[PDB]
Image (tube, grey):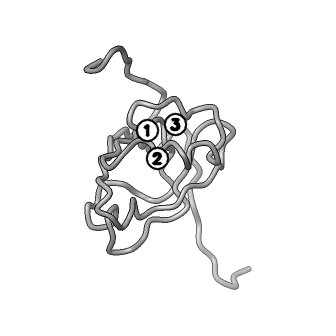
Amino acid sequence: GSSGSSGPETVCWGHVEEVELINDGSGLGFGIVGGKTSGVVVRTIVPGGLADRDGRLQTGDHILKIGGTNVQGMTSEQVAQVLRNCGNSVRMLVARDPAGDISVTSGPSSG
């Protein structure tokens, strides 16, 4: 680890990509939601903002860590304060296409 000590997290996933967002006064541009009992999720990502423009982070992205923080295990409510403290530049580990994922199917007023 660059600073003090740190180690990478390898978990059964299909697509692991790191997203680095820099608060430009406006904000990250994405909400969080404590879906799973371990980790945080992205409720939504403000359109044409910071995350959107970048085109790196995607909605409902299982957040593994935050700027080197152990969130996986705590409640989002506690993470909300972590993002702020983290500072201007934030680096969270988002992953998608998890082993045995659930396929989404549409059906407006069907059946």
Do the CB atoms of the residues marked 2 and 1 lie less than 8 Å apart?
yes
Q: CA distance from mark 2 to mark 1?
A: 7 Å
Image location (x, y in percent) of residue 37: 69, 38
Image location (x, y in percent) of residue 16: 37, 38
Q: Is residue 21 above or below residue 31?
A: above
Q: Residue at x 29, y 53 (%)?
A: 22
| Residue highlighted by disc 3 | 99
Question: Which amino acid type is marked by label 3?
Answer: Ala
Q: Mark 2 or mark 3, which is nearer the start of the sequence?
A: 2
Q: Secondary structure at mark 3?
A: loop
Q: Secondary structure at mark 1?
A: strand
Q: Mark 1 or mark 3, which is nearer the start of the sequence?
A: 1
Question: Which amino acid type is marked by label 1?
Answer: Ile
**10 vs 83, nearest the viewer:** 83
Q: Is residue 42 above or below residue 76?
A: below
Marking on residue 66 = 1
| Residue highlighted by disc 2 | 83
Q: Secondary structure at mark 2?
A: helix
